[PDB]
Image (cartoon, rainbow, N blue to C red; front, side, top):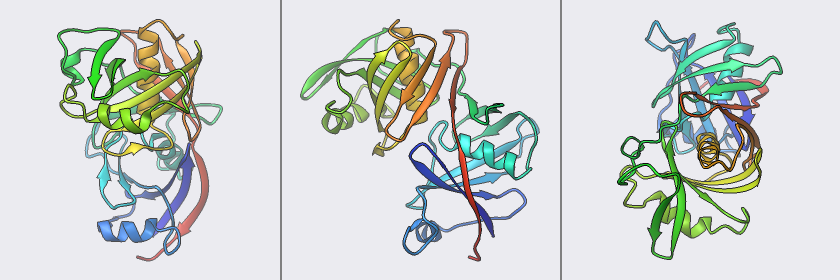
Length: 274
């Protein structure tokens, strides 16, 4: 079996062509391959598959080191786009792809970066889902230790964005869990902590739904910028600094889709018989 190793902002993936190859991995095999000392070594596994839909170009699944399939809006999108391009699985500039959760359109920029069309941000509370009487630019959320103000929005997945003075000392450890599993968020939520440096630059930390804080949560960068723009604290093109690295977010407001742009790097190609 052939595979490629790639990385994008804090995460390193093993990407496999599951289109021209029939691939299957027991959760066990995945755990073995993810092991950095006895296996290939990687944070997540990405399989490119047929879409079984004449309107899409591809589909792809992501598995964590535990061998479980996961659905994180936008995750692995850039590595996927560069992989199908490099491997000649497609030659289009705009690629339609579906993930376990939703759909996306990827654009391979001339500068070699990947621009992801994340669609229009969803504000209606009920559609997030988030329990609230009506829409608000800033919602009052009570937690056992503090009442916080936050913007709430959906990029397919639920988001809670709290602004903080200093990203390094923000109480992510305690507020993250309290927000992530707050009652007013029926299906749980991704809790973002945003420090605004200026109208076109922010630093972000995310306590991902069910996974906690990691090196980078793209959909989180999207939500944070969307909220900031909605509140009038940010311009329409913003650089987001996640722990793993930076992303560029562009959103022209309601009626427009939000774009997320970043890099994806090919490292090497491998062959392994399972």
